[PDB]
Image: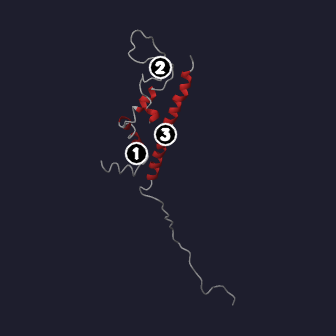
């Protein structure tokens, strides 16, 4: 008399197949790429030109002496 | 030819991006006035020694004093 089949309690689990967790698509990408890229170029011309100012300063001490 | 940019950018999207960097690179050095500031600096970098010359009568300009306003003005860069 002690056999298995239970009265209730069932799901089931799915046979489904989906995980569309997107994801900033469709022209939202290529937008964070370009602006941060020119931001790095914007970081230039305030350092290389600044080091160029120090570069003439470095060559200044050479020319002032040597007579 | 209007879909020709939309039947290869959905077909081979690698060299299409190369030709756009082949473009926008040849054209722009002839466009913005930030160039020729590249030329004014790259000539005004003193390597060698500026040797003075001999006076005889003239004197058109530039006496012996270095801190006199007697030469050019490249001092815009320090103000820049």
The residue depicted at 59 percent of the width and 85 percent of the height is A8
- Give the mark nearest the N terminus, 2 or 1: 1
Q: Residue at x 42, y 57 (%)?
A: A26
CA neighbours of label 2 inside 10 A, class few (<14), some (14 to 19), many (20+):
few
Whether residues under marks 3 and 2 lie with C-beta atoms below 8 angstroms apart, the answer is no
> Quick one: which residue is furthest to the top in this view?
B56
The residue drawn where x is 45% and y is 35% is B79
In the displayed structure, does residue B41 sit left or right of residue B30? right
Percent from the top left, x then y, of residue B65?
A: 47, 19
The numbered mark at residue B16 is: 1
- Quadrant of the rendered structure where residue A67 is? top right
Q: Is residue B35 above or below residue B12?
A: above
Say which of marks 2 and 1 sits in front. Answer: 2
Q: Which residue is mark 3?
A: A46
Residue B30 falls in image quadrant: top left
Q: Are marks 1 and 3 on the same chain?
A: no
Disc 2: which residue? B65
């Amino acid at each position: 008399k002690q056999d298995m089949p239970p009265v209730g309690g069932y799901g089931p689990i799915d046979y489904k197949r989906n995980l569309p967790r997107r994801g900033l698509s469709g022209y939202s990408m290529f937008a964070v790429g370009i602006g941060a890229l020119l931001f790095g170029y914007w970081s230039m011309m305030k350092w290389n030109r600044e080091r160029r100012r120090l570069q003439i300063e470095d060559f200044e001490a050479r020319i002032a002496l040597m007579p | 030819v209007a879909a020709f940019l939309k039947n290869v950018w959905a077909k081979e999207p690698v060299l299409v991006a190369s030709f756009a960097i082949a473009g926008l690179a040849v054209i722009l050095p002839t466009l913005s006035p930030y160039t020729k500031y590249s030329l004014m600096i790259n000539r005004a970098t003193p390597y060698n020694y500026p040797v003075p010359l001999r006076d005889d009568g003239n004197m058109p300009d530039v006496p012996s004093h270095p801190q006199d306003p007697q030469g050019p003005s490249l001092e815009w860069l320090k103000r820049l």
